[PDB]
Length: 134
Image (cartoon, rainbow, N blue to C red; front, top):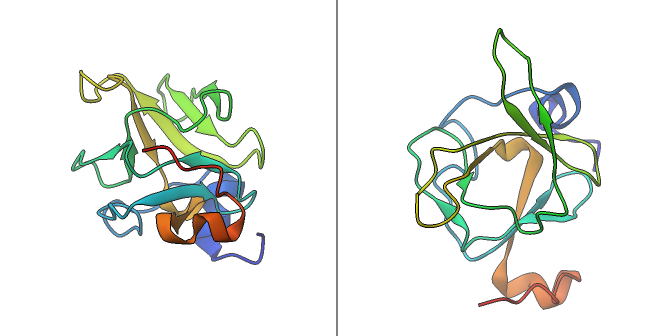
């Protein structure tokens, strides 16, 4: 919550992007939620994630649509849809229409230096408990 790795900070705060594959929640598929490394406010779950061999955690929708602000991103001679934390106003990364066609067809390619996983088994313990879906 803002004594965090140079890259945890670079991404969230300075609109950075972590190397692909050399990141935490890439291949991670444990059952629990992913939260804003800063706010702690829940941004995604574990059941709504998939393999995109893209280099970064990819998700089919967001936990709470009314809980990420999506901006246009003119960056690097391109158009695009940035995905940021409403709550912490920090950088997650972008969304794309190339997802699995029978979930959302949206691809929420999120940076891991802007997420801390929380396991399913320590939820009704760290005050997200409410978040039991499934």
